[PDB]
Amino acid sequence: TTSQKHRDFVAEPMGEKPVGSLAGIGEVLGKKLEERGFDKAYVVLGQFLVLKKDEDLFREWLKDTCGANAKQSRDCFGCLREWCDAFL
Amino acid sequence: MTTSQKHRDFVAEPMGEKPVGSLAGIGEVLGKKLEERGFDKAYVVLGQFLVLKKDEDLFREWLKDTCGANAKQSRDCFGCLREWCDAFL
Image 1 (cartoon, one colour):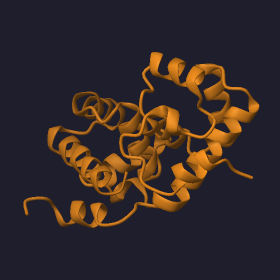
Image 2 (image 1 turned 90 degrees about the vertical axis):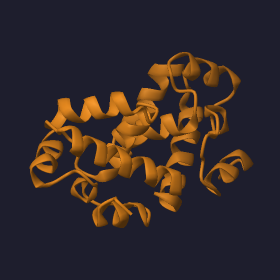
Image 3 (image 1 turned 90 degrees about the horizontal axis):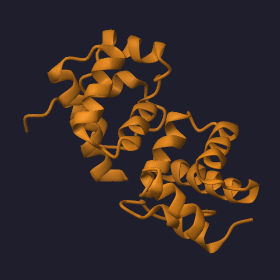
């Protein structure tokens, strides 16, 4: 199942939404992503796409980059995957 | 309209699973070199465009380094991705 945060993200183009609009990305993860250059949601989408939507590699990259746990990275992957199914 | 028809066709609709050669500026020669480096679908190149925060200088140099694109090819590819994003992202 899904959070409302997920459903809100997948419902519409992301535009310039901050990285914190992604399901799974809370205040702490968002800071660390911003610290490393991923300040907008679309930059994380960029990494998802460069990695050819590979779940294992994206979730591992997120853990290595901002410390996401398994639930957080599951949530973030799922929200980007569903967004892409609707808009890409 | 000074863009190519090929630009117009790409920016008119979501890209889905389109191959990299659907991008403006990406002919068969550049497209093969991109595919050999793992950039086989247009959305993978979109991904690089986005990871570079849509920066023209960085993206155009990355394209040159990765497939040998010249100035016009890299401008066309960048402009096609930028307009696609303005329409759909």
